Amino acid sequence: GSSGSSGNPHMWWLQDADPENNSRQASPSQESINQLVYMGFDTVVAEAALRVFGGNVQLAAQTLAHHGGSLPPDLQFSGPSSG
């Protein structure tokens, strides 16, 4: 990955409740990511997680929790892995 510690602005303070939230494969949603960070997962991990599991806050947590921040190092046969 890449160092993550203060850089991009959170942006989108308030306003606009639901801009575009449909049940279709696509990038994650701030909230979905924010809701993740809450559980105890670096945003990056949250965003990366959602991406891993397509974009399921649960699927992510289900793992992020089970594992406990770190993601599955053996989730993808050939891909990213600390090892």
Image (spheres, rainbow, N blue to C red):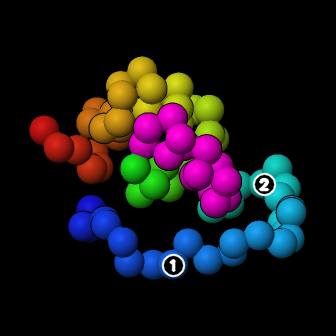
- Check the image and report above or below for 69 versus 55: above
Residue at image mark 1: 9
Mark closer to the chain start, 1 or 2: 1
**Res. 48 visible in picture:** no
Q: Position of residue 64 (x, y in %)?
A: 44, 32
Amino acid, disc 2: Arg
Picture coordinates of residue 80, whole percent (x, y): 27, 50
Kind of residue sitting beneath label 1:
Pro
Please state if 56 lies on the left or on the right of 36 as rendered: right
User: Which is more toward the observer, 19 or 54?
Assistant: 19
Residue nearest the viewer, comparing 59 with 79: 59
Residue at the (17%, 43%) spot, across then down = 82
Q: Residue at point 44% right, 38% down?
A: 40
The quadrant the C terminus occupies is top left
Q: Nearer the viewer, residue 27 or 30?
A: 30
Classify mark 2: residues with Cα within 10 Å, few (<14), some (14-19) or many (20+).
few
- Residues shaded magenta: 28-41
Q: Is residue 42 visible?
A: yes
List the residue tagged with mark 2.
24
Q: Nearer the viewer, residue 16 or 66?
A: 16
* Disc number for residue 25: none
Residue 30 colored in magenta in the image: yes
Q: Residue at x 45, y 26 (%)?
A: 65
